[PDB]
Amino acid sequence: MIPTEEALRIVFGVSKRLPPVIVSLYEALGKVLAEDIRAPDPLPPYPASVKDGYAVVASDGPGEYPVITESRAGNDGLGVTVTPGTVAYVTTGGPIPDGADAVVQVEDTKVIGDVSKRVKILIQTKKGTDIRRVGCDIEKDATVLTTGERIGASEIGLLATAGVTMVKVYPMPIVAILSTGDELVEPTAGTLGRGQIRDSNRAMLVAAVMQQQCKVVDLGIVRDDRKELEKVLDEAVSSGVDIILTSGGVSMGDRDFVKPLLEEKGKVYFSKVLMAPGKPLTFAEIRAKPGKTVLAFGLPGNPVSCLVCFNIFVVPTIRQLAGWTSPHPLRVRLRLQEPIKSDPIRPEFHRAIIKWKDNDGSGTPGFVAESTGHQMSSRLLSMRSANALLELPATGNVLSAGSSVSAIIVSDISAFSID
Amino acid sequence: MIPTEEALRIVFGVSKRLPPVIVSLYEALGKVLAEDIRAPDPLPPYPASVKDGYAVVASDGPGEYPVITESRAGNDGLGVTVTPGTVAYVTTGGPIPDGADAVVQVEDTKVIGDVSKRVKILIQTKKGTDIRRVGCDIEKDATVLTTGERIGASEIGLLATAGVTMVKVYPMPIVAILSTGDELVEPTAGTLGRGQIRDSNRAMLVAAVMQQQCKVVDLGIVRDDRKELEKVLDEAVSSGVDIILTSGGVSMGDRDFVKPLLEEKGKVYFSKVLMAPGKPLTFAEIRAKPGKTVLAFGLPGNPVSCLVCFNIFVVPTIRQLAGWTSPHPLRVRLRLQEPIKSDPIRPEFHRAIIKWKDNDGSGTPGFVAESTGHQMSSRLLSMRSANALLELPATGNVLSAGSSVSAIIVSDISAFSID
Ligand SMILES: Nc1ncnc2c1ncn2[C@@H]1O[C@H](COP(=O)(O)O)[C@@H](O)[C@H]1O
Ligand SMILES: Nc1ncnc2c1ncn2[C@@H]1O[C@H](COP(=O)(O)O)[C@@H](O)[C@H]1O
Ligand SMILES: [Cl-]
Ligand SMILES: [Cl-]
Ligand SMILES: [Cl-]
Ligand SMILES: [Cl-]
Ligand SMILES: [Mg+2]
Ligand SMILES: [Mg+2]
């Protein structure tokens, strides 16, 4: 039985980034860049007006002038030179005609006469005003994105700016998932027979892996039969998946075949971890027959222990395989809203609902946590709406309301419900 | 020109939750529940062993006993009664045979004899030990999930536990997106002609809306022609979308037709907002001809202003339409890592890269922010890797390094890179 920090170190050490692939622009969203991106031309590639108004010779100053061209896009005003004593109409983003060196916004002008257009410039501007010189936003050949950078909406915008519609990225791993147990029935089952429960772990893990943006291979319910489980594991290993997640069949039962099968097919690095919830957690590395590595997590059957182990150990593995340079979860410090009794032996991943408050109970703003109630590993209601796992050290003491603890954030911080 | 708080209030007031729909279990992930979910049977539905070991009569105490049945699942041990002086083998989750009232884990036992199985119980247990009574995790008819609750991995697990594979939820809105401008070319363009730039806003917004888990209707580049834009807007309004996002054609240019077209087709509530970056932002409500409401955001053309307006105004609208009870973004308080000059008029949404530190500069842990550099609205590099918008009030003063500010978190807090 090893501590969680060592189990994490072992997993990190074995887990290797996947080979990069080439994807389309919209397929690159959420993925980590596997190449630098350089701008092939400047932004703007022509001197561009910041305003709707008139391009002028700054030294002319206030006065009445003829409008000699109109420039909004493309070739508008090509071959026209704005000489002293003339102006040109411009819209925001419109090319500045040759000879003009400043823009006066339309609010500081007035159109004069009926019909040959004439405008009155009402201010004394300065050379360069309200003009974006060539490459002022992005210089030609500048690096706009680098290897190891995750692609979000702004990064897609930068790729589109640079004319990149096919992108070299690190792919997401493909994850196979199965449930084990003679007591399991499908979640479509209505009336349950004696000694049956619905398989909840498989759908829970399919959803958890879909939230990590990975493809899922659903291998269904497997019975507590060594030959049957070996066949499904052999089929999973040869299918091309990168990660296998099983649940159950990893405790001390006489028909728990996941750990001995993983010892036979590959290298098991650990089967037990010092923590609450649970204890059994097998991690193995299997070589597929040519040729590649498959990581296997023999997750515990208890629904809570299953999802907590997915959150602490599988999520950083998915991220490492997908090329994340920072795969660890966000850890914050927070104050307890109620007292919690800590265990004298097992450090606990206590489920909580956390929120940011203007006063965290100490007079200054901060996160605060509410427990989800009873933490028994069989009680999936303790995971309901939990957006954090409080890291409670094994002291045996009651942590009073208002005391500060470390907390792992397990669900979208941008999706946090406000206080 | 109205303040951002009033523009937000107006948007919230007009935006209505979409009618609920029925979806499959995996389609319900990310969606908000539109019904309560009750457990049709208890969990566990039979007295279940917490351990792999032996079910006993607690009052028997330590001694040697015959093993009269084995119980792992289903009908194992049905019709067998564990009487005083007998025991039954059990695995975790296995049904407790009639007459047994406690479980002794296999570690506190030893098998005796060769071959008729016999076991030695090594401890004095207590009635109820290591048994999950019927409904101890979930009682029959208990409410396991409620209306207004967002479905994540644990909630999918609870739906599977309760045998619910078709779920009543609030759907995501469908969003139409178009770009405007005679200066635009597709992002596939190689060498640019004079006065052209690649359309970056459309792909940026398509990606931003895909991150909000909404279906996208890509309506492409529209030119600065009033009849052409009216036709594309009429087609968008009649297509069945809930939200329309345009960008550009909303400043003071003589070919900016988005605002006058939105005034003609529906009700425009505002066209200008007091903020930095930018200023133009049209919001309108259109009635589709029978019959439903379509919300239109005439977003600014400047890439930064376009994405910031999407983040502050469109994201809470998507969430309100999708039935979120808490659609506002997470706001935290943080310390500046560098000095920032605030504007004397326009309150700013200053882009920053924020991280949680053990020491935020004041001796206690907290978030800290680094500016992304120059904040010009034409500079999409200022959005690069920005996970927050610092809310800088319009004071005209320099906010020194170490001063605290309010910050809107705009990207996954669970995806935050650690310090
Ligand atoms: N799709 C787009 N991608 C990049 N820049 C744009 C886009 N649409 C408009 N712009 C720019 O945003 C600014 C304001 O646009 P407008 O409001 O149409 O004058 C101008 O500099 C435009 O060139
Ligand atoms: N797919 C599943 N869904 C819900 N509970 C499960 C699942 N698989 C195993 N369990 C339960 O988790 C506990 C430990 O499983 P095991 O390690 O197979 O003994 C037992 O109470 C099982 O009934
Ligand atoms: Cl039945
Ligand atoms: Cl436990
Ligand atoms: Cl060309
Ligand atoms: Cl601006
Ligand atoms: Mg089992
Ligand atoms: Mg335009």
Image (tube, coloured by chain):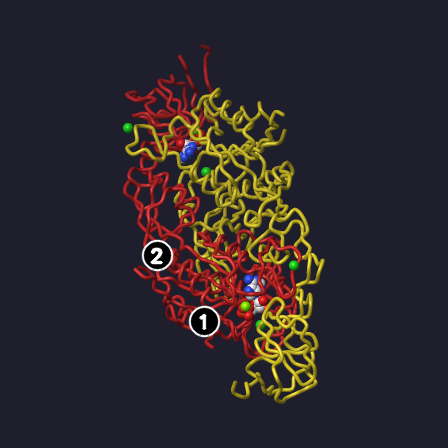
Chain colours: A red, B yellow
Q: Which residue is mark 2?
A: A18
In this view, the residue in front, A145 or A202, is: A202
Disc 1 residue type? Lys
How many numbered callouts? 2
In this view, the residue in front, A17 or A93, is: A17
Judge the density around disc 2: few (<14), some (14-19), many (≥20) Cα neighbours within 10 Å: some
Residue depicted at 62% across the width and 86% down the height: B65
Q: Is residue A112 left or right of residue B139?
A: left
Vertical side of B20 occupied by A309: above or below: below
Judge the density around disc 1: few (<14), some (14-19), many (≥20) Cα neighbours within 10 Å: many
Query: What percent of the width, then of the height, locates residue A145?
Result: 34, 48
In this view, the residue in front, A383 or B411, is: A383
Disc 2 residue type? Leu
Vertical side of B385 occupied by A15: above or below: below
Vertical side of A201 occupied by A167: above or below: above
Which residue occupies the extreme right position in the image? B141
Residue A324 appears in view: no
